[PDB]
Image (cartoon, coloured by chain):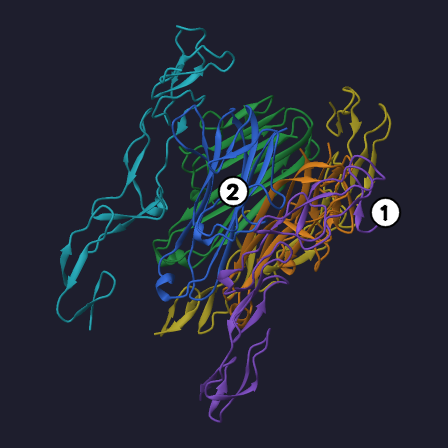
Chain colours: A green, B blue, C orange, D cyan, E purple, F yellow
Amino acid sequence: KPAAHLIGDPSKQNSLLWRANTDRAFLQDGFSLSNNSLLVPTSGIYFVYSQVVFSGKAYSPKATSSPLYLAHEVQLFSSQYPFHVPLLSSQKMVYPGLQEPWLHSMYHGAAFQLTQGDQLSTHTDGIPHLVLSPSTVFFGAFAL
Amino acid sequence: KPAAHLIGDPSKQNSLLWRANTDRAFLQDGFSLSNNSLLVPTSGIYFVYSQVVFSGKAYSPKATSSPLYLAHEVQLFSSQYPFHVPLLSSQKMVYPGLQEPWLHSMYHGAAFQLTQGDQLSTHTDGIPHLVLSPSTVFFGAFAL
Amino acid sequence: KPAAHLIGDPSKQNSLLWRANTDRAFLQDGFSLSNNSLLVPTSGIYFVYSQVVFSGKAYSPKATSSPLYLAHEVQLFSSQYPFHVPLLSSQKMVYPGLQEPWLHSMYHGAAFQLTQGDQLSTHTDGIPHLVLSPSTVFFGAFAL
Amino acid sequence: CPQGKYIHPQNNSICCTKCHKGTYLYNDCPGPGQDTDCRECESGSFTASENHLRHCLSCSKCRKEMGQVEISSCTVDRDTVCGCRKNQYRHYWSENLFQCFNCSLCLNGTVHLSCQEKQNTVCTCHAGFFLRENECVSC
Amino acid sequence: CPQGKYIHPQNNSICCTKCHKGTYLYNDCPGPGQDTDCRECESGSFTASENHLRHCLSCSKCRKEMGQVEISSCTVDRDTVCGCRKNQYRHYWSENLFQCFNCSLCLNGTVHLSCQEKQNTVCTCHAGFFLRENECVSC
Amino acid sequence: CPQGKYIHPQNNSICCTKCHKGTYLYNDCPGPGQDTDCRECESGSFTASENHLRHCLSCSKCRKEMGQVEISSCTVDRDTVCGCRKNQYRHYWSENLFQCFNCSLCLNGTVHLSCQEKQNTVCTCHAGFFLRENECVSC
């Protein structure tokens, strides 16, 4: 019954805000959005997924020295434990070349036993480099 | 009820044709294949997914100069709008080294509210470099 | 009804053993674990998925010469055929730089028509380089 | 039925008027002869056509890593237009992705062909110079 | 039950004859003593064994980026065989993936060991030369 | 209800005692005033808090590619602690990922600032030397 599909808001340049009012994004049967998190409406098994795409282009030799760490991760906040817990994490290290633009994509999804009230959120290392579009940066879940 | 799993046809060297008559590919409950597209049998929520794997090996120094752009994307064609719309896109830029073969994999999947009659298709930038096998290049969907 | 989510055991340094007794891993409705394989409880359609993350850091110039082949794959062993068959495979070639650590992630999932009794297992090329954590290395399936 | 109208989901034969550019189908028209409820896309959204879309499409950001710059802003019916600063040409990687490159000046040479929208300047080198892929290098 | 037969899905105890190589289970055999309906794999398919598969397996393409060449074509019961051109040896990356490399000639040296299927030629350099990982370089 | 207790899934108002560190909720407490069934995490598991978790969390392995070394072992209530060998400093890539780097010795110079936990040694070069990003190179 419950399902949600959200896209990264392309008008926010420095943060990653999820929204459901445009393109093919949606919420149905109880899923909802508070503090940039999806609130699980009922206990059960859910498939949770997310994708991010990053890009860049080192303009100076200083930028070509050290690598870039890119990571995206879906965390859970349940009343069962006082801390945020990672459910899925994807990581990549990028070594920028002088003037050559780089492009990378990361995707992940799995099934979990969630409890009504739990909150699902994402954390990203590399926000300034996201290619924000509805087909590249999204997050969602659906009950099995 | 409806679901489909399709593999890239390994006998077509220059195009990406989906088929369902070999290996573990299949169609059931109304999904069907016209003009290399999956036709959605009934309105509802579907999980749509696809994977591609690319490879290559630059034989000459000319080929090592400029990068290679690789992209795979799932588009939708609904009666609701006269144009093809991207639902999922994965991109990567590859910088070939002289004589060293490169290998990359891309995967994506999400849930959408589809309408009976809609058509799902893929577009790929990098077709000549696909590693065509049933476990590497596939496309599918299933109703939740 | 049946579903399973398993994580790579972080205490086994040289092998990839799946387990379901910690973190958010689980088995329900008939799925079970014999010889590091998931045993399909009833005939039907299942979504099968897996993710692996690899890392490394070449300490000597010898290690920077030849590339590293990384692959993860989900195979099926059905009574219908005497051999293991790949359902999903992800591959990547890595060219280590002297002293610069590398990080890569691979994910894959698709739907298949399975028969009760079939066995699902994984094969990995690059085991010594896995970043073993419950959010990075997992494997699972669920009936549609 | 009539091109400019579409079939009502829960009742074949009640061909509602489609929504025109700048708006989206908020609600299917009630009965034959009744207006379809279309609404104006919020800022950041757009629809450039006849549609019965439930949401508006997001306006495109230009690819900064590709050196693109936004020529026209996005409006409720025309999506963002990207390009390059003149004195730069475009190189298409795919039918939708182009990168902006600076036009060659032809130092130590003469402009043979001026820079185009999708082509770099062609130079002719001065005697004593080699044209090494769009630059003149001394012998 | 009898190895060479398999159990009928909807009725335990009706052990049908399995399909042999080159064919696939089109339909489970009707009743005990009745032939199982197996059909010949279309070109491009194959099955190299006793099976009750509903489809045939796709024939493998060789990995061109690995320099592989197809030795034997695929047939309805034997899958494509890949390899390298003789004068080349194989280097296995994984139990299934091998790349083809050209055999060393031993310029400025003498062949110590001739090239093998999975091993490069070992050379012995001439006095005045250094064997720098399969090539003789002058001091 | 009381912080230190949690609501029973199948019966609001029966606020069971939470499990404390080192253990996990094996079974919800039977009735008001009855002990909640918590069990000790197996070796390799841990829980560092009040919880009603059905499983224990896996102990973390340190990131070897980052040169990390394990300072404290994991216990049923404290997770593995990673770090670097002293004489090395940490460089944080993300709020959780740090790589260990060797501290500079200031060859051909004098230690201006000694090495810190998250900072390399700052050197001052000897006259006749250039400080080229943490090393003294001769003019």
* x and y, in percent, of residue A37 in the image: 56, 30
Q: CA distance from mark 2 to mark 1?
A: 39 Å
Closer to us: A62 or D107: D107
Q: What's the mark number on residue E1?
A: 1
Chain where mark 1 sits: E
Task: Give the image quarter of residue A65.
Answer: bottom left
Q: Residue at x 66, y 37 (%)?
A: A111
Locate the C terminus of chain E and report the quarter of the image it occupies.
bottom left
Residue furthest to the bottom in view is E127
Q: Secondary structure at mark 2?
A: strand
Relative to E110, residue B141 above or below = above
Residue furthest to the front in view is E34
User: Please, what is the three-letter code of the amino acid marked with disc 2?
Assistant: Trp
Estimate how packed mark 2 is, as few (under 14), some (14 to 19) or many (20 or more) residues with alpha carbons within 10 Å. many
Q: Residue at x 56, y 46 (%)?
A: A90
Relative to D23, residue F111 above or below = below
Q: What's the mark number on residue B18?
A: 2
Q: Residue at x 63, y 38 (%)?
A: A84
**Is residue A25 shown to the viewer in this render?**
yes
Estimate how packed mark 1 is, as few (under 14), some (14 to 19) or many (20 or more) residues with alpha carbons within 10 Å. few
Relative to B88, residue E4 above or below = below
